[PDB]
Image (tube, helix red, strand yellow):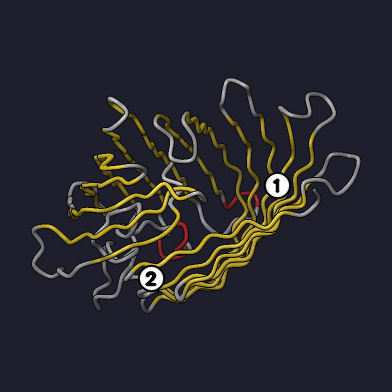
Amino acid sequence: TQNTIETGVGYSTDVGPRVKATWKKPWVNSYGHSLTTSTSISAPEQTLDFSYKMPLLKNPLEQYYLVQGGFKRTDLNDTESDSTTLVASRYWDLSSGWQRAINLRWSVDHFTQGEITNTTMLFYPGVVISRTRSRGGLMPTWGDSQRYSIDYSNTAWGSDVDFSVFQAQNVWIRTLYDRHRFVTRGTLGWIETGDFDKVPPDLRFFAGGDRSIRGYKYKSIAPKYANGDLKGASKLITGSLEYQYNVTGKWWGAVFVDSGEAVSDIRRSDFKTGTGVGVRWESPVGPIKLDFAVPVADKDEHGLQFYIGLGPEL
């Protein structure tokens, strides 16, 4: 067919309801080209992207250009942002599973972080290497994803700020005796810059929240200003261990521990840890999850955080 509407929904105690919706148009001409429009909506973040794919005649499934553009509005913690991005990319897929991409990103960001207000126009190249593999379906019995990236902004060719961003993340799924499923998750982040105040909050690191540190409020962990407002971190390390047990039928019970930090001086570790129990049901439409988590050994943070939605899990 010609148009497709995918549509997810979510809820969590920190963020509230959350709806995504994508509108894919798989062919637009006999030149292969395709278009995806996406939009996400929650109280704190709202997004609207477009993504235009153009296959190359020589090896059309392996190689393609991408043109993505987006708007984003953020109202979260001590962050307030208007964002507009454009990306030209060159992708090399392999049957070997690895996607390799060169990026050329443009953005204008109007933001307030705490009491600092700025307007940053960025223009930078970058590289991505990624691979997601799974086997056993929509709630895979086995799989892993890895994304590694490097972005390099320099003032020499028009960008507002000199910075280097390095990113890494792993997700690992393994089953043992068809009944004991283990989800393992790892995330590294690092931005080297002499002008952190000019960097948009999107490019700063914050920790906590679902798929970061369950039990802590979404993006609530990071260095503060002298006034106490959230500043954002130049370094992120977060991780999770989850064990899942198939109770009966398509019903699983899960126990998990997340832990991590967002710091600007890696010699000053401030590691926050969260923990909880959950349920997974393999619904006809994909895996539905439900998590309860509390903060662990924390004197300023307490309180149950609870989460529900259609998790991609990888």
Q: Which mark is residue 15?
A: 2
Q: Amino acid at mark 2?
A: Val
Q: Secondary structure at mark 1?
A: strand
Residue at 74% across, 29% down: 61
Lateral position of residue 279 relative to residue 93, left or right:
left
Lateral position of residue 293 relative to residue 314, left or right:
left
From the top left corner, tell me how far across and down residue 38 is, in percent: 64, 60
Residue at 17% across, 70% down: 303
Mark 2 surroundings within 10 Å by alpha-carbon count, few (fewer than 14), some (14 through 19), many (20 or more): some
- Residue position for label 1: 88
Q: Which mark is residue 197?
A: none
> As rendered, which of 65 and 224 lies closer to the eye?
65
Lateral position of residue 46 relative to residue 84, left or right:
left
Marks 2 and 1 in Cβ contact (< 8 Å)? no
Residue at 53% across, 32% down: 129
Nearest to the eye among marks 2 and 1: give it.
2
Q: Amino acid at mark 1?
A: Ala
From the top left corner, tell me how far across and down residue 205 is, in percent: 37, 56
